[PDB]
Image (cartoon, rainbow over all chains, first blue to last red; front, side):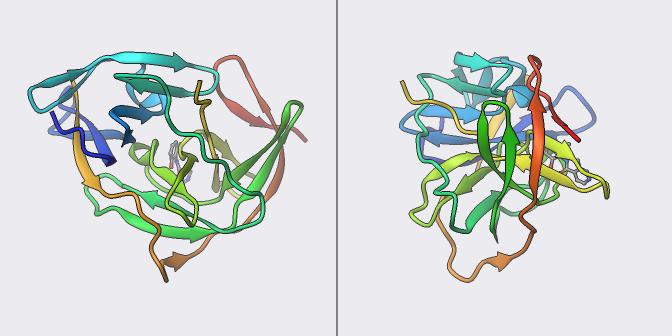
Length: 156
Length: 39
Ligand SMILES: Cc1cccc(O)c1NC(=O)c1ccncc1F
C-alpha cells in the first residue's frame, strides 16, 4: 500500500456509498488516528493491510504498523494550523490561536474550529510543519459551538 | 471494511485563512475518553 508520509482520509463502504469516518497521519511508516474513528479495527491501503499496534480509549488515540511517532508539542504562545480534511472536500490549512483546556491533571491546548465529525484525526501543526496533535476529541460549549483538544500521544 | 486514501502533504501554509477564538475552559476527562465542561 501507500506508505508515503502525509495526511489521509479514513473511509468505509459499510454505510451508503463511500463514507469518510475520519482522517489520519502517516509518519515514519506508522499510521496515526483517533481511536473513535476506527474503534481499533484493521485498515486497508490498496491491497495492503495495516494492523493496530498501540491504542488507548482514554487518550482517544491509535497507531498502526508501529509505535506512536508524533512528539511535537504546542509551545503555549503561537498560532497553529489545523490541516482540515473534511468529507468530500480538499485538504485546507486553517490558522488559529489555541485556547486551553484546564484539567485536574494539567492544561492542554484546544482549537475552536467547527467541522463535520468525519474530519476527526485531522492534524494540527506548528510553524515547522510538525504535528503537535490531532483534532476531533473535545466539547460543546454554551453557544452550541465546538472546541477540540490538541490531542498528542507519547513517543516511547 | 475501512481503507485509507492520501489527501496531502503536511506543511505550514503561509497566509492561510486565519480564524477561531481562544477559549480558556475548565474540563474533565472520563475513563471513556469523553471531555465534559466543569462549571
Ligand atoms: C462532534 C465532532 C467530533 C469530531 C470532529 C468534529 O468536528 C465534531 N463536530 C464539530 O466540529 C461540530 C460542529 C458544529 N457543531 C457542533 C459540533 F460538534
